[PDB]
Length: 285
Length: 277
Ligand code: NA
Ligand code: NA
Ligand SMILES: [Zn+2]
Ligand SMILES: [Zn+2]
Ligand SMILES: [Zn+2]
Ligand SMILES: [Zn+2]
Ligand SMILES: [Zn+2]
Ligand SMILES: [Zn+2]
Ligand SMILES: [Zn+2]
Ligand SMILES: [Zn+2]
Ligand SMILES: [Zn+2]
Ligand SMILES: [Zn+2]
Image 1: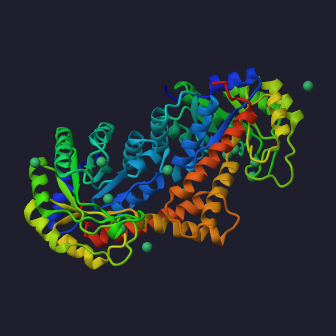
Image 2: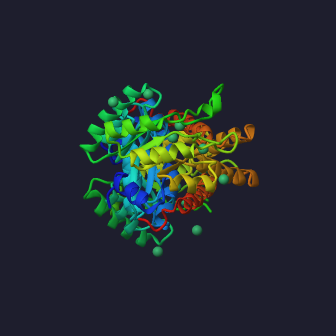
Image 3: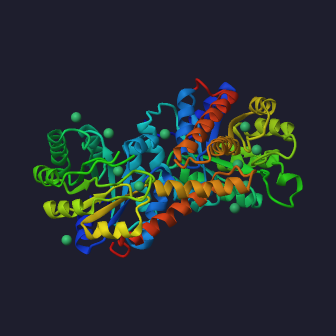
């Protein structure tokens, strides 16, 4: 079975009022976990790859080679996309595409609107010609940075959302509305009113970043307001490392890596299964 | 620049009186570290894959895809072999070969001699028809040690045409209880009786002098695994212990990978294959 873009799975999800989880890939065991979770739950799944993570894994080509081999050899039957997360530029998106990515996000939300539109439109030209899905962003997703206002959150402007989607033809849009990458300082403060307006006026699947720490009620609400893709990364790292700590603290002698990395991989699998069910994509393959 | 079998690199080591290290692969970061070490040292390298490690990494096909992609994308220019370590059966060696392994070890040393010979011959015929190098074994590596018999070595090499031979002569997988007691006189006989490169198993914990002495007695391939696991985990422990809060895996896997890289470099230099690429 071959890889697919995110087009079909996200449209099906929007119509079905559930979301497809993107879970970020970090290495080989991370990927086995995510795919195993998706297979067991009979759910579509998106493998997110940041440029940083791609470097950790040598590059886009190693990433694609490894995913393809795993799909074949694990017998994965469910829809899988490989999506470049927070693509820096046209050139990065093109490289990921040529390497065999089936989806890319061009994130130019930190640039002036008109530059964002221009860059994004260009990425879309190249991607759609190759049956690659595209995500873009408006507003700023929060983070763990120092000396920022409100964790660095800047709400998307629904009017710009409308214009950018109309001008570029992206397949999905991330309107940053309170998402923070990594843990939230307090309870997330998601702009559901703004989201409702972005849903009204774009008509495309929306993407909700910074999934770790967003309580179930906010997840259901976001989905009910047009969110069809939700990204989780931090939570997998947290659970992976908790399981690795447990093993290393209880047995001070062990050095066989699979004795601590295995339980960590299992922890990730169970974490992804939980989020899959929470998002409503189980049985939707 | 594709993967090669072990034939050329081991014959060069034998003539050059040095050894090529086999370093066992356990995952993606493990492979990156081994390849980076070899490339930096301009040294041939052998990537070892046990059947258990193959499974941990899903399978033989995933192993090959990963290595081939890393080779191209890291710009690896030195000789690299992928070697099924302790192949348990003809069928396992066939599967590895079919997946694109360039080298296999059929280990039937724990069966009667004539069965070992017969099985090994079967693997050699399949492998050599595909330019795949073959290792076989006599005697038992500790994990209890049993010395290979030099006459059986002569006969097995002659009957099979294997490219290299592991005469178990004191090797122990993992840490040695005391200090190794290698059968150097036995090894010399095997060297002389066979004329093929010999393989030293259980390199972790074999002191420098024993290594240099094994090489002078015809050892051209030296397997190392445990020491990489020890250094990797040691580096992980240091990070997790000093920082009770960190959860980002690259923060501890990263230094684990560095530790392995440094360990392989040291072993490559000790084995003498730096600059032999
Ligand atoms: Na978050
Ligand atoms: Na050893
Ligand atoms: Zn890294
Ligand atoms: Zn930018
Ligand atoms: Zn415009
Ligand atoms: Zn994000
Ligand atoms: Zn948790
Ligand atoms: Zn395993
Ligand atoms: Zn038998
Ligand atoms: Zn036994
Ligand atoms: Zn002598
Ligand atoms: Zn061995």
